Image (cartoon, rainbow, N blue to C red; front, side, top):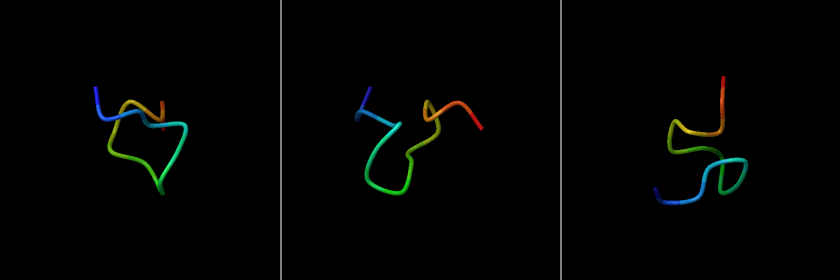
Length: 15
């Protein structure tokens, strides 16, 4: 959720 891999990173940016 959010999107991650993106705006800085929510958390699901994967590390």
